[PDB]
Amino acid sequence: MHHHHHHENLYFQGTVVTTESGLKYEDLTEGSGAEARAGQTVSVHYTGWLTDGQKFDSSKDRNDPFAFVLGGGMVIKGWDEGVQGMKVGGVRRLTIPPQLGYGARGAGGVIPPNATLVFEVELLDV
Ligand SMILES: O=C(NCc1cccnc1)[C@H](Cc1ccc(F)cc1)NC(=O)[C@@H]1CCCCN1S(=O)(=O)Cc1ccc(F)cc1
Image 1 (spheres, rainbow, N blue to C red):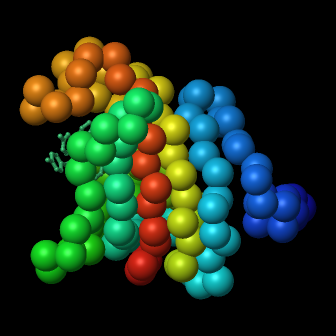
Image 2: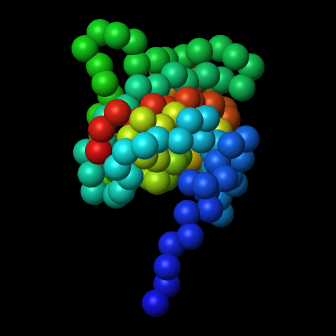
């Protein structure tokens, strides 16, 4: 029988994980609550930037939070992969390569073709 070892949970400080897809992430704060898993409707706060510091979007007050079905293709691939394994209360920084973001199409004329994206995401509910 396989057992989980919780390495990334125990030694998260200053740790940048690079996955087989090429996505990179770092837990800035480890969450205390439940774990995000595929199939769940999750709610989050977020800020997105280009590598050079230009902000392109944020979960501003309004009536947010932002919510989506994990693993269901409602968002960019780096988010469907990156949010899985976060715990409620956690803040996670995602560095997303263009293939896991908007690729060569870009978005709205604000995010250019072939852009790497940086996001800081806070998990509120699962
Ligand atoms: O595109 C989406 N899904 C389609 C899809 C599915 C599979 C693969 N590829 C695409 C969603 C839905 C959305 C579209 C447009 C919006 F304006 C707002 C939401 N978005 C996102 O996935 C990311 C990540 C989660 C927070 C929102 N953003 S985001 O901040 O980058 C958007 C943005 C981009 C450029 C801007 F100038 C401003 C906002």
